[PDB]
Length: 306
Length: 306
Ligand SMILES: Nc1nc2c(ncn2[C@@H]2O[C@H](COP(=O)(O)OP(=O)(O)O)[C@@H](O)[C@H]2O)c(=O)[nH]1
Ligand SMILES: Nc1nc2c(ncn2[C@@H]2O[C@H](COP(=O)(O)OP(=O)(O)O)[C@@H](O)[C@H]2O)c(=O)[nH]1
Ligand SMILES: [Cl-]
Ligand SMILES: [Cl-]
Image (cartoon, rainbow over all chains, first blue to last red; front, side):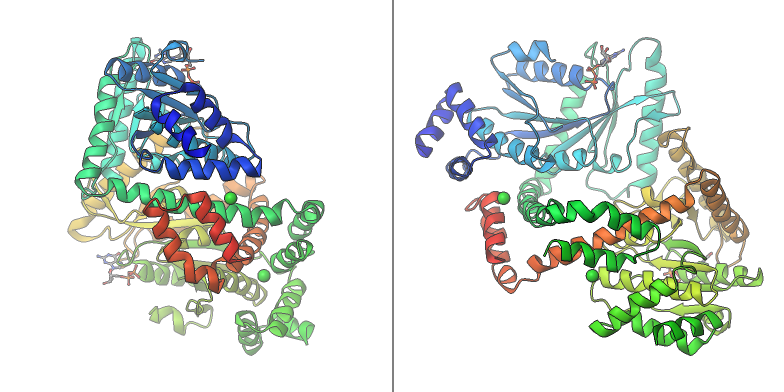
């Protein structure tokens, strides 16, 4: 069963791949146990692809970029999978590309878990580059950052001195920043904004930094700057491997994800408790109104979940 | 008992204040229950001071700044308390200043809880400005940000084009940024770095923002720029009150702190569990070595805590 399924994936049996993917997406406890045995078997193949995260707000040009980058990597001999943690016509028909929409959300955590595990199945099937994308609602960027080696952030220049749609905790996550839509009359403004952002990075990150994120400009549509974006991603990996830090980071990602599953399980028992859900609104109001102190309110919530 | 103690604090009895402060710092369950009843009684006085956070790395000039700002506010008729969540000779002898070192740490959470509650006792005693400081080890800045209205970040210019000691998730927390030590031969470099940081803020924060953080220069030692730092803090409050957003934010801080106490209690049961503490190292190793998947490792940890 489990071990035969692994070998079929290793052989390139696409049907075994899809079976296994449905197997890791499954909510049943027989499938869950099966999924983990599978992932153990496939441990030698785990890690064998480059992991690249790609984020940006809607309208930045993320689909177009991922499509153009996917084709450019396929032209270079890679096999590319694209996963969403939350269309591309050219890529969906290519035999050496794999495209899965984001899985129905048990939670962000459920989707993430499914994506992480599907990454291993795809590495086993021979995909050597995995692009993981997110639009960045809520905790989404932080989640993708924790499963990739290099996190690429796509932005737009509003003008030559302003960027748009930079969310609260996002630049810090970026290993590469791309000012996209640098074509036509707008090319001018995009390059000046990119330079200005380089200035900000030089100002703020210690000169001593092992890696400081490059700012690049690109036209996803025209394909200019795409080769350079890819060289910068490979450069990042090299600098990290060269520091003996590439594998160290992946091992830390795995441990951190272990603990976040422990945290989600323990916190869910409280947050989804029907009695907590019933009183929580009234508890929060009573804190807002000063009728209850926060410590008393916290004790009331813990009690409700007792 | 409880209600008489409140009135003494309200009257300005310093002995009742210290009693109550030891009462909120106490680990016993009779004192804890007493503390919360006290805080309920004092609910009309809660909130009556300005809450100002002040962070920066060691060597920035934070003690000197807090001392100079404290005196400047006392000269203006305020009564000032300074609390640490983790020396000032002039301030420690003034009758209208209050200085408490950081409380011995049950945890960052314990220290924070104690500081938050002591803020209420101080507001009751007539202190109308509370400065809350931290050096920024670990989760410290985020903790202070969650208990103040305006968070002031102190930095140093390494040169005229580089800042120093900017930690991972900190600029985002700042409502005001100060480039300190802008005196002598170095004044030149400090002002150019401040301008450059203003450029970065204009580049990155939407022009539409209700508040975008000002960058100021200061000499804590000479006292130049201190009045201006204080005007900018008052300006922040005004902009927030004017948007009808000042009280809304405080109410959100209280609710968020309620939940973080619930989270700490629930997570501590697992993390401090002796069986979890016994296996955790070996579990993490087995994940690192690929002998265990993360999901299996998480299940092993949850089981150990069963
Ligand atoms: N001018 C220009 N437009 C682009 C570029 N890339 C994408 N677009 C356009 O921007 C719009 C959104 O593109 P899409 O890839 O769907 O962005 P997404 O929402 O981030 O996925 C589409 O109309 C694209 O044609 C580019 O490099 N230059
Ligand atoms: N040149 C200059 N030195 C300062 C200034 N403020 C503080 N210092 C010096 O910087 C050192 C550290 O000051 P301190 O307030 O203890 O910094 P802290 O570690 O952040 O508390 C001391 O030697 C101060 O005299 C300033 O405005 N200008
Ligand atoms: Cl509690
Ligand atoms: Cl689990």
